[PDB]
Image (cartoon, rainbow over all chains, first blue to last red; front, top):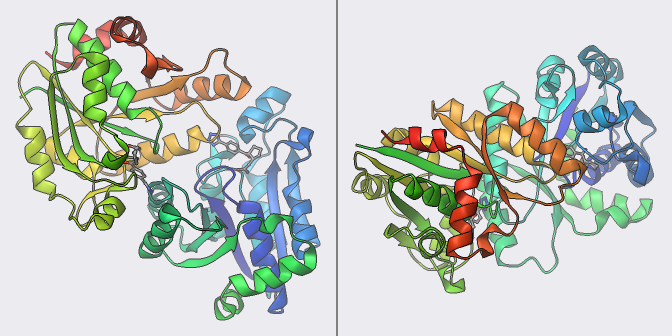
Length: 226
Length: 227
Ligand SMILES: O=C(O)C[C@@H]1CCC[C@H]1C(=O)c1ccc(-c2nnn[nH]2)cc1
Ligand SMILES: O=C(O)C[C@@H]1CCC[C@H]1C(=O)c1ccc(-c2nnn[nH]2)cc1
């Protein structure tokens, strides 16, 4: 096998997709083969497609998914509004395990936060992480309230013995501000801050995003992932 | 002693203060003596005074504060900016113990979410609730992402055997969209929703706020809080 990392977040809209793209770009530039799995995607009616984002930003081609739901809701709510169940737990775990191979970094992007239901009955990305023996990278914001949501998420990981690979601030503001600067210092006292992506990084073209990603992550940490 | 309830939330600005006032108002209309304490209050340089708001909204007179910091930040950050220390864990416990009283409902309003540090080193409202054997009333939003934060908060409570007294939706929109309606039904299956306060309840005057508060909570549940 290779390395499987679930990329979760403290909640919704925190930067999970752009962090997945940034780490994939950084890993590829270190020579690592990268695959990204988005088991469940919602909000397709308005055009949401996180895998296509990763492919355009980081050039990844191994992009695996199982289900797409039109409504921009939690997967279980989007599934219910469409009248079709979520995928099975076996579907998600086996897709991830089949993606995994030696020399490869396989990133699993969840929907919303860690305890969001992704499969029936009540299966979350935390359950998936246990099943595939993956560590968890936690995407956090720099905004008011992030320390509480980070601590809650890390405790939920530890409660099921899921290792934490570190934190990433999904959007670092410019200029930072008092709360943002205080939060970044405190976040590093909670867990290892692997990167802070500049605000607006999701809008970069592929070449600019690759330069940003290469500078945002520590090269020794990236190469050490596989 | 009486009944101590810590009033926490899934995060910052979710309605902890208005829920404290609503439950205080509902208990006072049932004849229950209510005290509300605020161990750590930040944002005083902005005029934030949750105790003053609770008294203004619900008519609570027994209001007890402890630590006050100017900046509208997390307690640890607001204290550091002011060159001040956070209170001790026992100081928060003493604040609550001196209010505790048979026949009285003592609400302990937190700052931000459950794992926010209120005392050094890393002492949170969850630790306080263990010290004073209080249940925890969790204020949640109806907005996108609330189920995850609610589940995370309830799991944190269980991890230290802090009983969950229930959930309160801090602001319930009218009319509710698909997300808000979905979230409420899902929330009611995660735990018992004690009330869903209408949006803008914080802007009601004394008379209207009391009428809203009485209608928002099950009278049997409120009455059974204190014997
Ligand atoms: O992936 C994201 O974060 C953004 C997507 C964009 C479209 C919907 C978002 C989503 O999938 C989502 C996941 C969980 C929850 C939730 N958790 N607890 N209550 N509701 C809400 C939304
Ligand atoms: O009580 C509230 O929520 C509102 C008050 C109003 C003024 C600041 C708010 C506060 O006290 C507060 C508490 C914790 C955090 C936090 N948690 N994790 N990172 N930062 C942020 C703010």
